[PDB]
Image: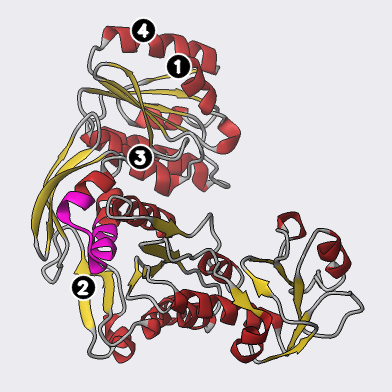
Amino acid sequence: MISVTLSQLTDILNGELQGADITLDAVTTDTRKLTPGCLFVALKGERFDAHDFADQAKAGGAGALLVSRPLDIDLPQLIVKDTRLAFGELAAWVRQQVPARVVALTGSSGKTSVKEMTAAILSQCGNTLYTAGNLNNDIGVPMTLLRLTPEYDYAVIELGANHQGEIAWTVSLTRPEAALVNNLASLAGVAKAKGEIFSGLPENGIAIMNADNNDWLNWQSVIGSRKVWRFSPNAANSDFTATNIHVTSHGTEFTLQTPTGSVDVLLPLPGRHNIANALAAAALSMSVGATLDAIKAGLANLKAVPGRLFPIQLAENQLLLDDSYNANVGSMTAAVQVLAEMPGYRVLVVGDMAELGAESEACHVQVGEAAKAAGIDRVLSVGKQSHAISTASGVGEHFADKTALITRLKLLIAEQQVITILVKGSRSAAMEEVVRALQ
């Protein structure tokens, strides 16, 4: 936040001042988050009118109240027509007051990893702020934007959308120098929505999109004549490319080719899909100045989310890939592809999937057949359905409990000096136990 006076806000938020003037230096919508003499914005959701929490905010030390009606609270009030709007507007205003290179992103999948990778890289460049958690809606964006100060050098704003019109609002507040749509997944309506992100770009702004997944046909009417950047590992029209992809026991090594040159980087996250994210992140970072050196160093310190292709170094050359969070045909079939490229003797350790009905048997068979065709060295399984996988893989063995698996697994680990293990199963299968047990 920046210091602002109630009288200045009457103009800014188009609202009436009903009390003395005051300087604010902090604003919040949460009673559990009051600061001495801050502005308490009383929002009204459907199942909550924070106006009824006015007295509490006063009692907490709130200096004034931003509200949509007069309240009998001995505190300077700023009566505006709509608080949802005013909150966003106040955030818009604050963002205009700071010198931070603001950049934004959306998509159907990967918003968080592209955000985190972009933030990780720009952090090598200067003081950077990024969206916290999944605060990407009409309330979360203002909250994120409101955290800005003259001390920030960069700002990575993640924008989410559920319906149309939503991103249009938030980018108007954010006014990013570069905007990115990571991907799409009816579909045209989602494309229309995410495409809205390009409307907040200045005339010198850069529109970035996925060469392998976009809606340029329609997005060109909103990006207009602005500069355009495309990322993809090998797309013909890609600006951010990935060559010499060599998967290692650590992560993926590759030559990242950007519009200014290339740098051989090490992406420490299992999964080829992270290579694309890294390209998006490189694009976003570079739009606001990041150097190749900054990109390489930013990527190099990424950490995976436990239970999701989470690498765990057992001993030398003994890699465990914790992907025990959940599992369905898609994520499972994909897991096999990840393992298949891994170094050494590869063991797919699995448990039942969260599949439904008569197609369950078939779904396990497929995954087995996939590991079979992938050349997986061995598949140890537990469950009353997962036998289908190990059976179909033409290799591997099945167990009646996880304890017998862990034992045979440990032996295999001691037996094979170079092994890559991938543990994965449905939530109900509780495969983390195999992972815990191993470490």
Check disc 1 and give the amino acid type: Gln
State yes or no: residue 114 in magenta: no
User: Distance from label 1 to label 4 (Cα)?
Assistant: 14 Å
Residue neighbourhood size for the residue with mark 3, other residues' Cα within 10 Å, grouped as few (<14), some (14–19), many (≥20): many
Residue 314 locus on image (x, y percent)? 35, 18
* SS for dot 4: helix
Q: What residue is rendered at 22% in x and 90% in y?
A: 225
Task: Kindly check if marks 3 and 1 are in contact, taking CB atoms under 8 A apart as contact.
Answer: no
Range covered by the magenta-colored residues: 279-294
On-image quarter of the N terminus? bottom right
* SS for dot 1: loop
Query: What residue does disc 4 label?
Result: 411
Check disc 2 and give the amino acid type: Trp
Front position in the image: 229 or 405: 229
Q: What residue is rendered at 43% in x and 72% in y?
A: 98
Q: What residue is rendered at 85% in x and 85% in y?
A: 70
Query: What residue does disc 3 label?
Result: 335
- Which of the labelled discs sits on residue 439, or is there none? 1
User: Along the horizontal axis of the image, is 80 left or right of 353?
Assistant: right
For discs 4 and 2, the disc positioned in front in the rendered view: 2
Residue neighbourhood size for the residue with mark 4, other residues' Cα within 10 Å, grouped as few (<14), some (14–19), many (≥20): few
